[PDB]
Structures are given as structure tokens and as C-alpha cells.
Amino acid sequence: MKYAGILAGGILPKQFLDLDNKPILIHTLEKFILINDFEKIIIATPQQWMTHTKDTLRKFKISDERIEVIQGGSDRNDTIMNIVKHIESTNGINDDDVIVTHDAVRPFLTHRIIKENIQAALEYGAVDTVIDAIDTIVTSKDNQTIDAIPVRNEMYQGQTPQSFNINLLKESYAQLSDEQKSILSDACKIIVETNKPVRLVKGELYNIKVTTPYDLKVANAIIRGGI
Amino acid sequence: MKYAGILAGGIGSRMGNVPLPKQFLDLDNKPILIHTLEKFILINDFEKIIIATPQQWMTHTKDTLRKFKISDERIEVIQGGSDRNDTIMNIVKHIESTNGINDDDVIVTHDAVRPFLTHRIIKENIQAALEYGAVDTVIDAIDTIVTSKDNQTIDAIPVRNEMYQGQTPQSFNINLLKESYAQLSDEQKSILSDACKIIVETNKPVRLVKGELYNIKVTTPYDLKVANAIIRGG
Ligand SMILES: Nc1ccn([C@@H]2O[C@H](COP(=O)(O)OP(=O)(O)OP(=O)(O)O)[C@@H](O)[C@H]2O)c(=O)n1
Image (cartoon, rainbow over all chains, first blue to last red; front, side):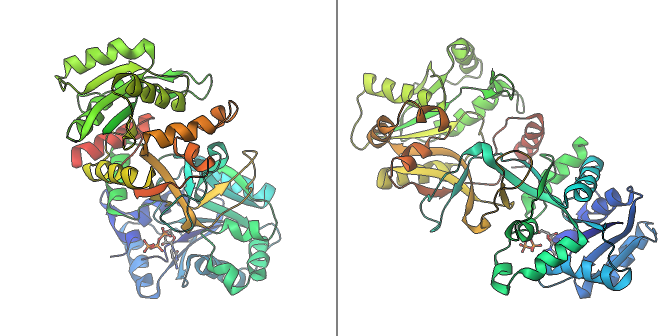
């Protein structure tokens, strides 16, 4: 079975800001609603915003019975595991279950990205949505001087969705210590650190994350430009 | 002395590595190249602003300078090289044959299609190059960076706090860059697309100067639409 997990547990908080007279969260959700194969599309948000989010869905005439709003966690991976735990306590986990986890503030993902994510999770178990690194990547351990500059052709910018077999995600995450979880910049590293493969799905240059005011200006350009 | 080297070699196509003259595309009724140059003319401390571009584009570059009334006596157009680093060295060699290199000379090298750099970025580059010899303009990674050696599976996912997206300008004390570059083999002349990697690979420090989220490289139609937004709005 196929599940969507829309991650709105972050901090008016950026996931509810208006983008073209419709909240960013709604733009993303609309993309997930058009996929009929999700058994449930689970939105996780902070406790104080859950009823407000449900109300905002009602405001935009979205009544799809597949949508459930749940309480998120204290960090991003805590939120993903909250969604899996909700699934486990509601439906139980099937051996073939997959979860498509996705940033609420990335409203410009496409049908193709979701379908490739779904298919990639079913076939290989774990997948990251990426594009070729737009810049040369440079590293630093002191924030003052370069430590290393890797070969540019091996570098990718991680985006979302990130998609997983639910049992694989649960068991892998269960293996990590609290310190090992302290560094995880994303969810796919849970899998990498537990020595299972993570597949690549190509994103889009316009699949941006709205985290600064600049990103909202770029997003407005993306929407008015139709892309 | 302080020199600017504006790198106008084009943007290579995935298949063929054909140079496309993206710097001549229109951004609000002025070529991208003209916006970038206008940013450099405002820095009074530059002794020369040398644009190096392929031989086949030099006349059109000069014609474009004329059409947009760019009359600054410091602007000069020269022939570029076989790759980005060879073009940088074409600029260095031109400086040496014209004025001669001083021990304190620095060169601020910059992508022609990065028109949104700021006065602060340029001044900080100059100061950092004078004091420390080598500088990369960078921003904190916003995305998690992931690696792949086969374009199919992840190889590693490093700590995001240590990852940065490199931009330009990249600025160097000229004799230092020359000495470091002179240390590289003919083979390493092919891999190193980046100019700061010359220095890193030759075991000299490179300072970080922080860039801007909007200091984008205008290389795609998508990037061009966003650039039109950035420009119209500030
Ligand atoms: N405990 C958390 C933290 C983040 N996210 C979501 O992960 C996505 C990525 O946003 P990010 O860049 O990681 O930043 P935030 O943690 O949301 O907030 P800040 O801008 O302060 O970093 C966001 O949609 C966020 O809502 C989440 O679901 N639960």
C-alpha cells in the first residue's frame, strides 16, 4: 500500500504563508491529492496548529477522506517517525507498504516526481529526489578556510520527496543511537548509515524550498511564469 | 594593484560541450554581461577590467560595449583560453605583458553571467585577496548535499554544516595563483574546472567570503525567468 506523508512540523510559520492567495501547504497537498493510489495522505503539524490546518482545508473545499492531520515531532525525522507510528497504530504496516515523505514548503513538485518516487520505493526500497549540483561544492570545518573541494560531477543537491518502504525505514531508524540521529541532515542518510541503497530520482530546478523571503519572491515568479 | 577578470567563455552544452554565449541574452533590455560589467565599473579601485571571451565572440562583445555606452577606459576585451583556468591565465599573462605583475597585485575573477554580485562582495574579495592570498565566494548549503558515483545510487551523505555552494568572484594574489597553477600537471589541467581548487590542491589556504542567495548563475531559461524577477524587485 502507498502512503503520503506531508511534513509541516516546522516553524506565522512558513508552511502557512500565502502564495498566490492559497497557502503553500495547500499547493503541495493539491499535488498529492491528484494521485488516487495513496491510501492516506497524512499531514503532520505542531499541536497548536492542527485544528487550524484542518479548518484551512475546509476553507479551500478539500474534503478528501484520505487526508488525516496528525501531531508532528520535535525534529524532522521525529515527524517522519510520527507519521509511520500513526500508520502502524491505525492500519498496521504491510510488507509492501511505502511512504512518500515530502516538505510542505516545496509546492512545485510534479506528478512525474511523485510517480517516479512511488515506483522507485516499490522497486528499490529507498530513493532520494535530487538534481545535479548547480554550484561547485566546497567544504569547510572552520567556516573560515576551505577544507576540500570535491569533484563537481559526483555532487547532487538533495530535494524531496524522499520515499521509503515503511518497514525498512522503521528498522533502520530503530538502529541509530541518539547521537547518530543528531547529525542527520535528511531522512535518506538513515538508510545510507545502515548500509542499504538509496536510489536517485531527478527533481527539477524549480522544486525549491520556501524558507527565506527571497524564496517566496522566487516562488511567486515560478507561479506567475507557469512552471 | 587591483585587476578584475570577467570570464565570458560561455556555458557548455551537456552534449558536445559547445559554448553558448549566454552572457549576451537579454535581462530587462540589457545583456547579462552589461549588468555584470556595470557592477565592476562602480569599483574605482580596479586598474583594469579585462573581459576574456572566445575569439569568435570578441567583436560582438566590443560592439555590445559600444551599443550600451560602456565607455570606461579601463574596460578591455581579450581572447580567452581553452578552459576556464586557461582563460584565467590568458588574463594573467596579458597583465604581465602590459603592466607587469606586482607582488601585491590581486585579480578578482568572476563569471560574466553572475550579474547580481554586490559592492560588498567585491570589496571583501579584494581585501581578503590582499591579506590572505586566495578567496572563494560561498554560501551555506541550503539543501542536504548527496553524493553518487554512478548517477543511480547514493554514495555518501556528508554533514550539511560542512557543505557550501561555491560562487564567484574568486580572488587571488596574482603571483600566488601563478605559482600554484605552475605546480599543476597537464592532467590536473583537465579536471579542475574551479579556480580555487588550483590553490587547494597545491596546499595553500583559501578564505571564505560569504555570497548571496540571489547571486545566481544565469545559465537556463528557468534561471533567466527568476533573474528577471530578482532584477525587477531589487
Ligand atoms: N520538527 C520538524 C522540523 C521541520 N519540518 C519540515 O521540513 C521541512 C524543511 O524545512 P527546513 O529547511 O528543514 O527548516 P525548518 O526546521 O522548518 O525551520 P527553520 O527555517 O528555522 O530552519 C519544512 O517544511 C518543515 O516544516 C517538520 O516537519 N518537523
